[PDB]
Image (spheres, coloured by chain):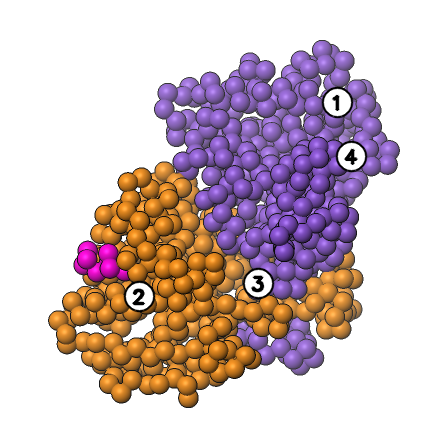
Chain colours: A orange, B purple
Amino acid sequence: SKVVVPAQGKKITLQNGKLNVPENPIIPYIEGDGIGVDVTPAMLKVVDAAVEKAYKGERKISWMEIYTGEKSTQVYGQDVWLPAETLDLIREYRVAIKGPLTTPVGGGIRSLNVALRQELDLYICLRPVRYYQGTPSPVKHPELTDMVIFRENSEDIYAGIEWKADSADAEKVIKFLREEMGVKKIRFPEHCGIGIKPCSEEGTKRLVRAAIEYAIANDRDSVTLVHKGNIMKFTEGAFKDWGYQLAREEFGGELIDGGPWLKVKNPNTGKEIVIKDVIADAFLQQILLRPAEYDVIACMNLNGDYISDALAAQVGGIGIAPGANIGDECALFEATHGTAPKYAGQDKVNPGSIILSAEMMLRHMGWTEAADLIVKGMEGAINAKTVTYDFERLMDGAKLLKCSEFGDAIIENM
Amino acid sequence: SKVVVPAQGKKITLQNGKLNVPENPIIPYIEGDGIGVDVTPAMLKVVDAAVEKAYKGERKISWMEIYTGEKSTQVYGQDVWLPAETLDLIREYRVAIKGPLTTPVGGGIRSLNVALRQELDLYICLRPVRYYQGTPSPVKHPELTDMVIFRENSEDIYAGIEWKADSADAEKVIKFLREEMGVKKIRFPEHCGIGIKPCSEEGTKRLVRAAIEYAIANDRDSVTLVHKGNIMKFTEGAFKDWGYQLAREEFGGELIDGGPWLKVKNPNTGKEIVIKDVIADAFLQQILLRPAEYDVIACMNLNGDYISDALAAQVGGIGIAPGANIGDECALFEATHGTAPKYAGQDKVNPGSIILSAEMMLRHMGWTEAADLIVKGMEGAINAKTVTYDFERLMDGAKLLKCSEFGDAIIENM
């Protein structure tokens, strides 16, 4: 209704579990607030150059701007932060990409990024983190990290189920817990906020299934379920058990030694994938001390959030980390950093996160060639030390490029 | 009743907020399971040598063994994992120290370490992490880390309030949430485990109060409240607001710029302590990229758990990290690592965690001199590269010592 659909261009189609991508697909993009105004132009330009180069003019993306966040209120009016037609247009065109998003405080508005994930049921937050050679790192051996994070997106304490201290609601549920359920375990029941943490069987088996499948499809070496199950037995500990059960039941997993670890034979390469588990706080220690031992990771919403932010910091990629939210019916690729308003409009932030999310988008579309040209470009620009301000501070002998120019530097190394 | 109280020795007394420590105090210690059998002898020996050296024979600790964990079932019978008299004896003698503890699986027994903390209301988990010069680290600059963690111990999802998927209880609370509270936000209400997350005003203001107080008493530069409040507004976000409120209300905090940060003038050194906050997942990134910016940290139970484990890994101290659980009526110092049963009895694990917890014990008792001799010993043994197996693997040119012998090496560098 305020989105203008491209006259040239054809909708991607879902013909039962498989994308049928035309040569001129319409892709919805959300520009993003803050520095989205800098990074999203850089991404449209390098993706265009990568499909122009890989398919020699046969394929072309018809980009369609849709709205969410601060720009949505400037287009539809001050009150609409998430238009109902963004949800419909992402549902319809199947794959979309977005920049950083501002959620307002003061108006009872819950996180717009988590709202897109939940409203569209994009239950997989996929976070690949690997080291790009030559980026400045705080650790001695960043090259040892090559992990892919499957974070569950639709349950955990992120479901937003909570009531304020001293609200009627809070008083009411605390009353139910103490009188009807007999909980004598709340230390101070007055002036007390309450949050609900759900974890279901369906919720964890659909995310773990996608994790093992990813591991078979890419011949990864192991799947690690991380959980804090010693303290949370019926939510986090239920996640590890349902995950091992699904590896037994659906993938024909077998005990290594006398457990708990399983082996799943890859039906294509013949190799064995270890299904193991580690407690979440020991895992935060293990990615730093023994990163080469881990590969595909499956975990719940909050842990997945902490794990990927932590891992993206140790490989030097807080600003070049890609991400995707994948459901059964659509997928949303995204800059995983914030809107950083102080730099907005200055053409200086790193466009690397949304560009590498666009290569995840292209690879998902089946446009592997265009996608390999982007990570080729990326490795070469970073190796050339022809780099953005955030990388140049920490490097010696680098050439400082604006946001837009690092875009050109990715095209030059293609 | 099976503890034998020392014939020589006198109880420490609490004479309103202040410990009155005799020259021959009786200290309860829990030996610990697993490698507790190796580390606790090493600690009794170096603490004895430190008080013998500092006070030239005037002071002496009368050690009293009390029981919890696997050793408790060998002394009181197979069913008693936590004797009621351990709780009483720690309450009574005021300060105790413990080794690692085995919680059994299969018998519905919840974490014995969290049970001691809750049952005794030791609401402060204090975790000091600093780098000891010369220990092998995975990061380029471990020397930049000097932080003290005030983790809340009595609320959060750690209160153990949860019900199994498909249990009657679970069905009942899910029914209450959907019908009486109107929650349409649980994605799959069948086969669903539920955990409760409480956060009260009293609970967070008593921990934040102790954090600021610590900062005044030791002239630390800042107190950072870390929370995941953008998603959990009424538990984690309530923690940051109550913490800033307490810094305004009780410490006379003033706005820096136009907020949110506050300044608290130290009434003894005249210096300004910054009260700031950072989101928990960005913080996990910031301790690795800008560790020199943080100092005292205040946070809830789960975050505090993750933060300290992560920070102890980057300074090389997964096995030499000390810790304390402090309440208004008693304190329990502890090895913060696990029972590691494969090494138990072999005299090879690092006794460093429980020894540095004993220096926290001595400092708490007011025996500062004996306590400075232990960290003097520690720095010198580690600097001598006269070290335990876990440190020697990662170092070149080290001399390998058994557990007991690293104890002697701490006494030799005193």
- Quarter location, residue B216: top right
- Residue at the spot 36% in from the left edge and 63% down from the top edge: A39
Q: Residues within 10 Å of mark 3 (few under 14, many from 20)?
A: some
Highlighted range, magenta: A407-414
Q: Which chain is home to disc 4? A: B
Residue behind mark 3 = B230
Q: Which mark is residue A43?
A: 2
Callout 1: helix, strand or loop? strand
Q: Is residue B136 magenta?
A: no
- Residue at the spot 60% in from the left edge and 63% down from the top edge: B232
Pair 1/4: label in front:
4
Q: Are marks 4 and 3 in contact (CB under 8 Å)?
A: no
Q: CA distance from mark 1 to mark 3?
A: 50 Å
Is B270 placed above or below A188 here?
A: above
The one of B202 and B61 positioned closer to us in this rendering: B202
Q: Could you say where residue A259 lies in the image, as x and y percent from the top left?
A: 43, 51
Pair 3/2: label in front:
2
**Which kind of residue does numbered mark 1 sit on?**
Ser
Q: CA distance from mark 1 to mark 4?
A: 14 Å
Q: Residues within 10 Å of mark 4 (few under 14, many from 20)?
A: many
Q: CA distance from mark 2 to mark 1?
A: 70 Å
